[PDB]
Image (cartoon, coloured by chain):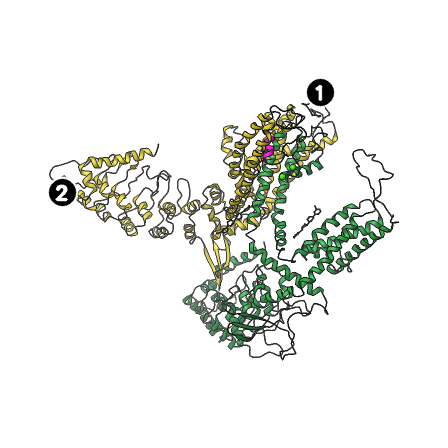
Chain colours: A yellow, B green
Amino acid sequence: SWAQSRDEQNLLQQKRIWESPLLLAAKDNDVQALNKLLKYEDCKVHQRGAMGETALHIAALYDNLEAAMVLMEAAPELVFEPMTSELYEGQTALHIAVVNQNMNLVRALLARRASVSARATGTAFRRSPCNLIYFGEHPLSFAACVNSEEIVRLLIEHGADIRAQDSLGNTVLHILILQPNKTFACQMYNLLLSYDRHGDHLQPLDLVPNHQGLTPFKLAGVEGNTVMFQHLMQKRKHTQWTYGPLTSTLYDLTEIDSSGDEQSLLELIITTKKREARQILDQTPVKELVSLKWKRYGRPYFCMLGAIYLLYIICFTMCCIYRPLKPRTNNRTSPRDNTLLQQKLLQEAYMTPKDDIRLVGELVTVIGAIIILLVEVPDIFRMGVTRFFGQTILGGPFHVLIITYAFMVLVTMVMRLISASGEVVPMSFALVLGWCNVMYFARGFQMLGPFTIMIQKMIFGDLMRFCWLMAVVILGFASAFYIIFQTEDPEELGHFYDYPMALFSTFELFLTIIDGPANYNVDLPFMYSITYAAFAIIATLLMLNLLIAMMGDTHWRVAHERDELWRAQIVATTVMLERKLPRCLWPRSGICGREYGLGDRWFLRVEDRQD
Amino acid sequence: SWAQSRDEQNLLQQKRIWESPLLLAAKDNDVQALNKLLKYEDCKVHQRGAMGETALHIAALYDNLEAAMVLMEAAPELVFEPMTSELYEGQTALHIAVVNQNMNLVRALLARRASVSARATGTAFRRSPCNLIYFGEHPLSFAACVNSEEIVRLLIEHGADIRAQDSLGNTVLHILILQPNKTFACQMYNLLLSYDRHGDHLQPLDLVPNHQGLTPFKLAGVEGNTVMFQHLMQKRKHTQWTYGPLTSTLYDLTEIDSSGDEQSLLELIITTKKREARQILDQTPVKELVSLKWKRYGRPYFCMLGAIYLLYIICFTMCCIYRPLKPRTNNRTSPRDNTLLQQKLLQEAYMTPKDDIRLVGELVTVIGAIIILLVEVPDIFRMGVTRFFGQTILGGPFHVLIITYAFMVLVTMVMRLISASGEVVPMSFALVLGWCNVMYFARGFQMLGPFTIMIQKMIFGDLMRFCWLMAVVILGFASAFYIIFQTEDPEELGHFYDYPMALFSTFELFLTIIDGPANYNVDLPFMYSITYAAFAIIATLLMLNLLIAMMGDTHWRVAHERDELWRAQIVATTVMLERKLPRCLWPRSGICGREYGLGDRWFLRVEDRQD
Ligand SMILES: Cc1cccc([C@H]2CC[C@@H](N3CCN(c4cncc(Br)c4)CC3)CC2)c1
Ligand SMILES: Cc1cccc([C@H]2CC[C@@H](N3CCN(c4cncc(Br)c4)CC3)CC2)c1
Ligand SMILES: Cc1cccc([C@H]2CC[C@@H](N3CCN(c4cncc(Br)c4)CC3)CC2)c1
Ligand SMILES: [Ca+2]
Ligand SMILES: [Ca+2]
């Protein structure tokens, strides 16, 4: 109902044209009608539209210079008045002729002293998918987006300012990144830098960030303008020597690596969501850098990190399988055919030196659980329960399990001091979520790990869209079996003797695991064989065999998507590694300056062949 | 850290340019600065670079003839001095102007008596992937690689030598094979043979091998230059008579078949590893030859070899299934429910004439085991244990099993004289590795054998990349089951009563083989049904059904790779067959000479249609 208020007013805007004789004569070139419209009497001028127009705005909007020339002769005061109502707020007639890419009227409006620095800050211009467009907030910002180059120089010549910024802090050089006509706007970016006369006081007009705090180079990395990124690299690199077909160049490397602050360049590529921008990882100075940093020093620190965790789980699961049990004392099997149990484990009996060996491993796993908590969820000293909602989707899928690995190991610290009955249940999740987590180390380790990016893409969606429709069908038949054996003895075919297990066992026949019941000794009810054969056609010949073919398109449709997603997680491992690991170890890559006459910013180089 | 020492020096090279006034004036055309740089005072010249340059080298490198002309006027002695430091070792300024493909300076350097035969033998030129290039070691070798043809004649005219060789023994005709711009260098190869005036004493400049011992024809077969191979065939063939559309030509056949020595041509194609060169098997004179030699005399010797081995295993397995057992004597089942056994086989009781029939077959299989050893691993008289490491990867995958087939048959020779207890275990591998080996004879035998090249490509990788992630998941749940039935009676659901079998049985449920446990008579523990249903979703509906679709791309992505790999193993069977089989049988193919006026080298012919 939000966008309804736009077009409700927008037809209503046209009503005032049909309502007024001035505005309807303004939409057409009614210069004969406009001649007598203000000469025969002193009719008023400032009658606004439904959303606050002048006829000068309308003559601008419906591309009519001629009546606007008569409107200049009638009343040359309308130019100062902008529009006023909440969508087109502050926009004046200088903007619209620029949007119309010429009207030979910037020759006329500026001659009538067109105010340039007005800020059309209405919400029909803010960067949002509710608008279909984005153009900035200044007339110099507009004409660049439509590239009317001759108009731009005349717009500059009467005192345009390059350094204008918006509420978002962006200047005109941020805007040319955001246009969707990529290469047609690239030569526009070269033109404005030619009109950079000087640095104002500190930076030479390209080094300025926004209110988000990003230079326009880094913003191109955010949106992933692949063509524009290659054009803005050309002043960063520095060719060194050429040898026939040999080319030896020195890339810059000061904007594209972690220098302290959280906004280098590479954190931004992982933390964004746009799939288009992840293809920045195949341009020249970055792909060589990340492959160098992963190979030298990057890979073996990850694996030797992984070797510790593998011994952690072994020291957990051996401490799991040894456990202070006891024979079943003081409690018979007095519930007959209900308790088939023998242990009811001990309470405080560690009086054995072999238990000290277990007392090692229990102490081993509990301290590392605190380490896992205080390295990835540090925001626990605040003690915020609603903070956990900002930790679920903020973080990867493997950034969820290992957190939940900790809580279960916290419970076996909690429970064994309290010594209550329920003990194997938190230990159960503690044991199976542990071993499943080792695929987090199967990210790299060889090229045998873009298998794991495939099973990630399949478990979300393409089995969850099957897990519903299994429960669609199977909740029918299981109750249908539950009725159809309701009159039956349990001691033969105890599959469906009660609904909580009868719901389970029909799920055991959907995946063909259990054999499918038959006695063949006494005669089963004569409606079973009908409805059960109905079950096997739908389940294990239609439904499940569809699913293998269902993967059949979602395995080559995403063929070269898994490989580009495999280059995602290595950078996501590399940047995560450098930020966690300190100095005097992991020497920061590239080659330093100050020794060779270059400067303080570091460098790397790549030698190749033109061919 | 190895290539770091390159670029550490390489920026440091540029520092001496920034450090010295001569070298910085040398990089630019500072002829006014160079005019006073040595006229105002007698400044020294031999100030080398960080890696040993002159300004003449730099003027050559940064394409500046003009200062080099002034450098000739200042001091015409720098040409004799080469570079000196370990990477560009021995390279002089004559090389670099050649790499720059002209400078109008070979007109000047040779006028100043440019030394031609210098050998730039630094390790920035040795054939290695550490270098990005390869160009040989002589100025005549360089200009051919960049094809500056006019320069080459002027380079020859002042006394270039064609017959130069390197440390690798290669001459300039080996070099043109190795360039990656294939057809652009082909006409270069025709030019140098035109400047073959005479044979030196013995060979006419094309018959010379390298230090590896290969003529440049055979080297083209090694690297697989498919276009260049077709150009070097044109002097080997000999057209005979044409009949309208009929064409009758006589190919050469003396360089491409086993003539004694181990380096004919066809051993080289199998023993190399480059996938590009195996596509030499579809040019004209080879594909017809190998198909002729496989069809006539080749195929039936392989199958009649295979028929012997099939009767060998039958005579093994019948000797396997008859075995000197005995009833269980002197040893009761005193470990109760631990020994369910009845035999504890005999020791030295062969007193039966039916055993002589078995004494045939035991003697049959043991002698052939020595035959298998002394035909494929002859290096056992040396008695080298570490030699076995040079026999594993050196040899095919079927060149491993049949070796390990021998050791197990050696153990049943060893064990039955010693008569210890463990007897069925080496016999077990002896029986199953035997029958699996018969796929080695399913290489050819019909076209129903590029199935076996497919299962080879799948068992390495595409199931081994699944065999890890099975053990990832299943080591969790099996311990998780082991906990969750730790308090449970074993006599009902004895699946998980101890961990070494509980590890096995959960592996029995991952491949859906066993039924999946249920009693349905007494009530199982109330956390089992939760975690077990969690198991079947992950295992037998997500993991295993992914794998069928995982083959789904790796069965048509390698579609016309298996057929080209099927032509590999037939040549690998043919060449293996000829080398093992003697003369006075397997008449060596082609048609002999000396009877028709041709000569001593043999020949074959192919008749076809131009169409
Ligand atoms: C994205 C991605 C990528 C790769 C792998 C994963 C894992 C996703 C969740 C993980 N669970 C293991 C055990 N679970 C469970 C344990 N007890 C009870 C219940 Br009910 C469920 C459910 C699944 C398996 C693989 C995820
Ligand atoms: C390249 C290629 C191409 C085609 C065929 C093969 C064979 C590869 C190995 C061979 N083994 C047979 C028995 N094995 C075994 C025997 N006892 C215990 C264990 Br554990 C393992 C493992 C596999 C099967 C086919 C290989
Ligand atoms: C049962 C099962 C199991 C696993 C997989 C499959 C199918 C999956 C993929 C399918 N190709 C996909 C589209 N095609 C194609 C490929 N390149 C270019 C063009 Br044009 C078309 C040919 C067939 C073959 C088998 C089926
Ligand atoms: Ca089955
Ligand atoms: Ca079954």
Residue annotated with mark 2: A35
Mark 2, chain letter? A
Locate residue A224, reporting x and y percent. 43, 47
Q: Position of residue B145 (x, y in %)?
A: 52, 67
Name the residue nearer the viewer: A323 or A507. A507
At mark 1, the secondary structure is: loop
Highlighted magenta segment, given as a residue range = A505-511
Question: In the picture, residue A321 is in which quadrant?
Answer: top right
Would the CB of label 1 be found within 8 Å of ligand 1?
no
Mark 1 burial class by Cα count in 10 Å: few <14, some 14-19, many 20+: few
Q: Is residue A133 left or right of residue A229?
A: left
**Is residue A43 shown left or right of residue B442?**
left
Tag 1 residue: A331
| Residue B437 drawn at (x, y percent) | 70, 53
- Residue type at numbered disc 1: Asn
Graded by Cα atoms within 10 Å as few (under 14), some (14 to 19) or many (20 or more), the crowding at tag 2 reads some
Q: Amino acid at mark 2?
A: Asn
Magenta includes A507? yes
